[PDB]
Length: 203
Image (cartoon, rainbow, N blue to C red; front, side, top):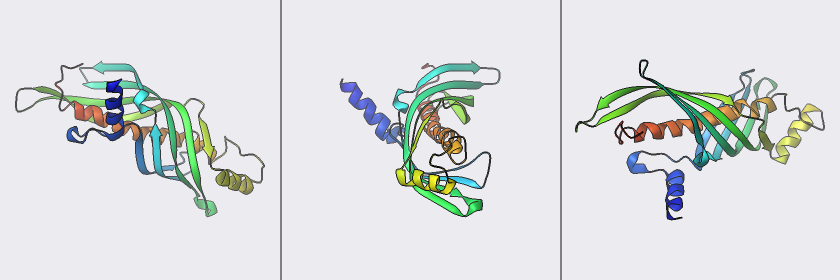
């Protein structure tokens, strides 16, 4: 349908005039992730491309007018691709290649809000800095380029890689959460921007 074309132009290009950023495809030029269990393991991503946010669901919305706080529970099936360097800093080793991830991400976005009027009597939500909590990444499917998976097998001394061993653990969990976090920065930014245009009424 006609509007399908416009929707995918909005998700893919944003809307600059309203300061609405793209969400699908969402491009992140670089992003580094430190393994939560060992700061000597650093994953450096470049040219990440994330798709699936256009189909995301807000599965719960909560609000408390005393604290003026909001919780949004989010669910998304994401397909992530990027260049990767795995730095095993204390071994002085670097492994390069390509990485993909497919999984279902469940998050919680929390933010405060204020209520303000514009030079026009129009009354708005002002969305404060948000936090994103990664609640579930399901059982993700991860892939690595064959040169990279071979180098890791070679270095490990084992025909097959251990998904529970580092750096694979981080690739299957923390890296997905950090990338989803970066995606939701755009999502929430779009909420924040559209709330400065639309009046607080529009629910």
